[PDB]
Image 1: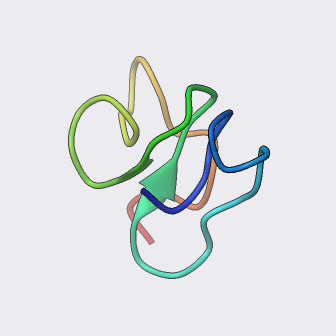
Image 2: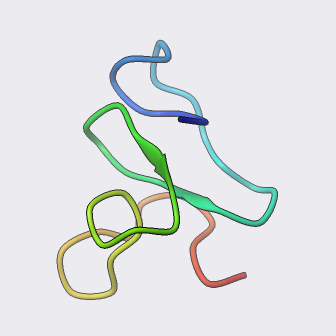
Length: 43
């Protein structure tokens, strides 16, 4: 976890990706192209 509704609503700008839920990473839940990509996804 790096951001989301669980971290106090932050943003991921490192290498992984956050979404409006509470999880940030690389999996197709926090970082999706058709269902996610809220933070800095893909790079």
